[PDB]
Image (spheres, grey):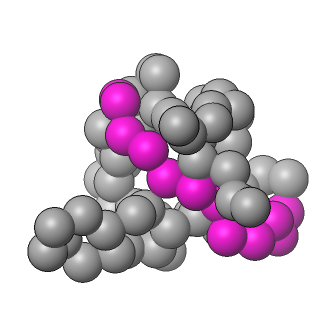
Amino acid sequence: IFDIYVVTADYLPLGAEQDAITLREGQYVEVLDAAHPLRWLVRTKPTKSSPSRQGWVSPAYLDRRLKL
């Protein structure tokens, strides 16, 4: 249903960004809703006991990826 994108160019916020979320080159996260072409709403998937976080990211560094 959703689309899990992967960071293949790294994403480290330089300074203090509001409504932003940190990401590591090689992470997976499906998109929730598409607001503006600049940045879409996404929420990482929780695993084991890690809480799920939601933050806006730039799709200019996210590539289409499908899960098994």
Identify the residue shown where x is 33% and y is 62%: 16
Looking at this rendering, what residue extends furthest in the front direction? 68
Q: How many labels does the image show?
A: 0
Place of residue 4 in the rendered image (x, y in percent of width and height, measured from the top left):
58, 47
Which quarter of the figure has residue 65? top right
Q: Can residue 20 be seen in this view?
A: yes
Place of residue 62 in the rendered image (x, y in percent of width and height, measured from the top left):
61, 34
Q: Is the magenta stretch mostly helix, strand or loop?
A: strand
Side (left or right) of 40 relative to 7: right
Most foreground residue, 26 or 35: 26
Side (left or right) of 39 relative to 50: right
Side (left or right) of 61 relative to 52: right
Identify the residue shown where x is 35% and y is 30%: 26
- Please state the extent of the stretch shown in magenta in the rendering: 25-36
Place of residue 8 in the rendered image (x, y in percent of width and height, measured from the top left):
47, 22
Most foreground residue, 48 or 58: 48
Place of residue 47 in the rendered image (x, y in percent of width and height, measured from the top left):
24, 64
Which quarter of the figure has residue 63? top right
Q: Is residue 58 visible?
A: no
Looking at this rendering, what residue extends furthest in the left direction? 49
